[PDB]
Image (cartoon, rainbow over all chains, first blue to last red):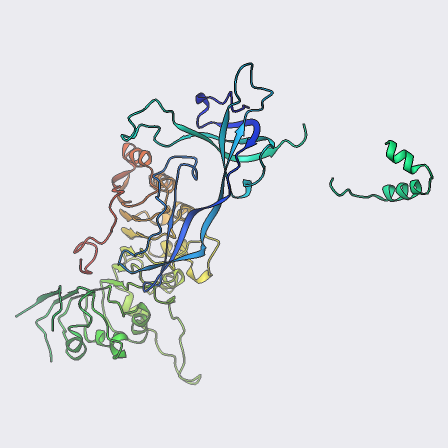
Length: 198
Length: 320
């Protein structure tokens, strides 16, 4: 049980709960995970699954976002939307609760990744508790392009659930008790005083 | 004097033959837009012919007798038949020939491989009668197919039920049969699956109970062999104890989990002799190295980068 401050590199790849406040909700985007293709002459429906550092809890070789357009036999392929599978994808930046941040320090924050039915569980400003797996991703400047290797690895929480902390009725239900007492009260004269003074 | 002939028609530009024992006709499917020996094959007879191997030729649409394999009656005693990537052939017509004639006294081996996905072919067990006051036509499937040691049907759109019916009818003997290839067949599903028409199910328990002493299996490219479906093979290990050589390569679904539990259960039989999982994306490196370290397979192949299966001359006679 953590917050974006006390979430620490010792916790990487462990299952964590973070108490915080939502900021910078990204737009929802559809993320391709399976592409389905009718083969023009072959008749078969070929397909391809896709991988990245967010779609899987464990590392697997990334599949780089390309639709295949030719069979092994060279026959051309027509991509099938609807049969192809896309998941909703969204990023939210959970900020530390400013009440918890100690003297003279800014609040830390981290990016939660949310897929499909966890998307838009919250909006900016919502106090929230998220549970997910804390992860590293990317090359962290170990790739030979980066002369500067003091930069740290990117890190995330891959979300497994999003609990909005609304508590520490917009249209009410009405029972026969309510119907009776509303009408019985309405026949009294001082309702304009009693209700307003309530 | 010519007993063995091999025509390899790499390119295109524009009577009784008792001597002949083996005919190979390999044709570049891109270039050879005809069937070179068609008139000879349909007219002549080649009675000594032990082996025939025809690949890449395009069966002409204009002659339905060619499409119905009527020529193929001309070759009795045909110990081996290999026929592959001949674009306009069909297993559908082939099984009509197997239905309506005692075309062969003995095939030791059959290898039929159409390329495109033709419509679903089912074993046509319909036995009509000319009249109710007359006998039915004898269906010659058994006496044709009884002898097979090797059955290869890779890619042929055969439905799983058709193969079970070959086993339940015992058209395939089961004792004589010792090696089986049904890779790349999309119309094969396994009893653990939930999303199918029932006639595409291959009851592996019924089949493995029928043909139990087979040595070699090939299910390569069979995407339908997901990890859940592999559980059928796990529980059916007692009915396949003769298996030495297994090919399930170029499967982009089968995780190393199924490999390990299959081999652990197989080891309850003394390791498996040979396993091919080249090109499989989900066979984890640590798992296969544990397979080697525990010596659960005597040889296991894991060339992840090997894109293709059709080793020419070894695995396929479709040209290049």
